[PDB]
Length: 20
Length: 339
Ligand SMILES: Nc1ncnc2c1ncn2[C@@H]1O[C@H](COP(=O)(O)OP(=O)(O)O)[C@@H](O)[C@H]1O
Image (cartoon, rainbow over all chains, first blue to last red; front, side, top):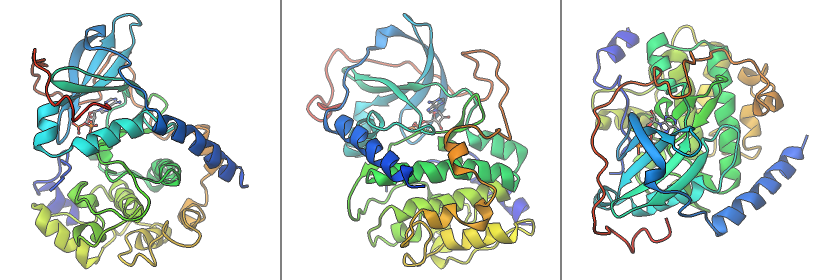
């Protein structure tokens, strides 16, 4: 499921902003 | 019902006065006792502090002047403070004081004890539509206000949305906020919330905030963002494609609204059309929404965080603390003169 794939990804925590 | 036009007109006069002659040096470090870190982002930290003379708690955003320069955020930091001190809206966090010393820049805001929407969202999993709708309406009105002052927010996300004692939203972090007429080009924001025109270095406008609102609404309702992957680069590929998929539980109204916000075609994106923000406000998904009531904070909040004291931080995660240093030598004096 999409939920499962999200939950198992490395971006479920607080996300940092970028400035690239 | 165009008192909103008059409302915005007076709101603009108010903003311009402060934008023209900004507040400065309204406090100093020793007037506060630093308690604990509430959160951190790309740079600097936000600490819960207690103001000695009054006894009130605040959230102090601390910025190391040297780190600001290294990351080339001078102009952005000056924008942040200049804009913050000039704005005034029911859903914008209040800047109470601001000042600087040899090493750092300080922006003292009102302390929003409810915590980030992020934590609640991840914990509960996802919000029901009425719940998400409640928050969405607040952002819609906030962007209408900011946009009317020629401001672009550029950093919408659950992490920057705080819940107050009444269960209403308080937008924080104007680190990327900018006052601009026309287009701009900075590649900034959070990967999952970037509009395709930002990624394609084409130049963009306020419309990017409306795309981000779509991402936000989707994430609140789904529990996960519309475009996600382990690496930002993979994320940009999905955003650029535009191909979106909606959870089975999404109502037809929600999906129609989302298809109009997560719209790659600027000539078609809601909020960026002839009728502007009214295309969103008048949408079927927002039919039950009483806009005036929301602005007046008279609608019952679907969620009211547990309040355990004026300086309670149980709604925030814990962070590794570190000493707030102040050099005996002034750093970047000329660069931050107007702060
Ligand atoms: N007014 C506030 N009240 C309570 N917590 C806050 C407040 N402002 C910020 N925070 C916390 O600090 C975090 C970072 O604030 P932000 O302006 O984004 O600073 P940074 O530049 O470190 O990202 C937020 O995500 C939040 O958890």
